[PDB]
Amino acid sequence: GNTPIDISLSLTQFLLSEFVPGAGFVLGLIDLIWGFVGPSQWDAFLAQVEQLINQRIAEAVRNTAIQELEGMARVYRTYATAFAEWERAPDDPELREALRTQFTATETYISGRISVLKIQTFEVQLLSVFAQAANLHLSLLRDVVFFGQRWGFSTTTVNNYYNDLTEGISTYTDYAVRWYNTGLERVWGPDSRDWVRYNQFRRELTLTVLDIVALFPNYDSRRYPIRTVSQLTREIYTNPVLENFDGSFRGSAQGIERSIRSPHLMDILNSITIYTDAHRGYYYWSGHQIMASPVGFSGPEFTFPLYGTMGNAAPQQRIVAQLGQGVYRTLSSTLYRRPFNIGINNQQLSVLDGTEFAYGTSSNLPSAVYRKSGTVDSLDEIPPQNNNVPPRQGFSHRLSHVSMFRSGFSNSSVSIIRAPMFSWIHRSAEFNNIIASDSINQIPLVKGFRVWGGTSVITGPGFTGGDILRRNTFGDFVSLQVNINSPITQRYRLRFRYASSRDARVIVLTGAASTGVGGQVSVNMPLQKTMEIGENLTSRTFRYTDFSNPFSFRANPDIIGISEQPLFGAGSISSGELYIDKIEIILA
């Protein structure tokens, strides 16, 4: 089993860590995807979303798509070797000229024939190979913008390729998120079964499409002259009780989706205290409590409201999640009791009767076990990024929350449903905000610890790899905690990635005060209007500041605050919205 979900996760790992242009990058794209000779690989890629919504692609359209993929891999392969021979004698004017034509030949082939992956009425099924190919096209355009003057191309030829890269990022992004959403809505229905297949689409295409799409902007090598590491803070969802049910509870799907928490700052799951109930010698997970900390463990634990019902047929069991790299895997045992319809006191049960919590770790640390283990295995839906090493080392996601979809009390109620919902954040969403020397640091604003009043966390547009922050008025956004590995004397610069339907002014303060409240203004920067009032959030509505003017922190676990300030003379009324996604920090 080498699923497309497997391949795509290892590719997410590659792009996230070793994003820097050179032979290592080309050799890497060959090894993970484009080295494959023949059709079967692309056949599997299409099959996954095809059987997901149970519509196969028309065969003429399907085979042309597969054969153009083959040709794309095939022209890239010859570019890649021509690239390597050049990097072995980089000044030779003949190797240069040989790479220059083999580049323009391969770019024209890929550029021109992506079309066959955007075919009308088959947009969703073709989405995952389109994401692969758009990502391949962008690798090439980054290459010329970065190596143009070494290769021998004119500065005018390169500036045109650069505009292609710009537009490519914006066009490809917008197509993918558009067909992601319309494919999602088409799967939605009102039943337990309809929600399962809805969520299956969301999860698989978040892994196979959106995560590669979130990294496209890093292909802009004029905007990112050096290394940069993005962070995927979005959470994908599993539910063993519902995903393993053979029937379907009717009209539930709207109730299930609401039981997921609303957009929120990123937290670190600390512990889960499970409560047990019983009925007729059948013991089950009836409710639980969740405790979390902010990013950086920057202060006091938050305890979530009770999930489910606080049973006592056994004593509570407190499972600590946050050991090593967190819980990477759950193996649950489901229990569906179907009696000969007695009722109320001979109940119908749709619940969990055990779960094993497996730790992500380079160690022998044993799993946590509630009652007993099971065979409903989350690793089957959230696979490893590296199958060459044991799962506890090559895992892709860490457990981030546990909610519950509840129905009935044990009371009356002929029927009881306790369906715990497991949230998975991608591994790249680090526990701390660490400012690296030597790279371009991305800190999504969802990594702060406090949202100030009148800033909302809004579900992200689809290409930021997480949620974002909105203000309707001017005011304070977040406070977040930063760690430097430099003397406090070291100087830094800062830029924003924002969306705004108005002009505004943005400031970053750096006097600490845990809780946030303090601060001294260190950075003052303008935000030009990026969209019209009431427009939708597409990639063209997002903009980068310049870098900021050197500043320094004033503590080494520092507490910085972001606020948006009224422009002088504007009269203190603000109309439109302000969106901030990311701040990025560099050195010197």
Image (spheres, rainbow, N blue to C red):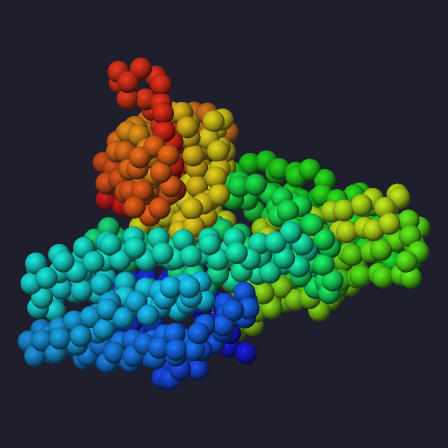
Does the image show residue 514?
A: no
Of residues 172 and 368, the one drawn nearer to the viewer in this rendering: 172
Residue 34 placement (x, y as % from top left): 34, 76
The C terminus - image quarter: top left
Residue that appears at 35% across and 23% down: 574
Residue 112 vs residue 529, the one in the foreground: 112
The image quadrant where one finds the N terminus is: bottom right
Q: Quadrant of residue 62?
A: bottom left
The residue that appears at 24% across and 50% down in the rendered structure is: 223
The x and y percentages for residue 230 are: 38, 53
Q: Quarter-wise, where is residue 585 in the image?
A: top left
**Left/right of residue 322 with respect to residue 265 in the rendered view:** right
Query: Does residue 334 sit above or below 479 in this rendering?
Result: below
Residue 123 visible? The answer is yes
Q: Relative to 414, is 450 above or below? A: above
Please give the name of the residue rendered at 85% of the width and 46% of the height, measured from the top-left corner.
413
In the image shown, does 323 or 148 lie closer to the viewer?
148
Q: How many marks?
A: 0
Residue at the (33%, 48%) spot, across then down: 539
The relative height of residue 90 versus residue 324 in the rendered view (above or below) is below
* Image location (x, y in percent) of residue 78: 23, 80
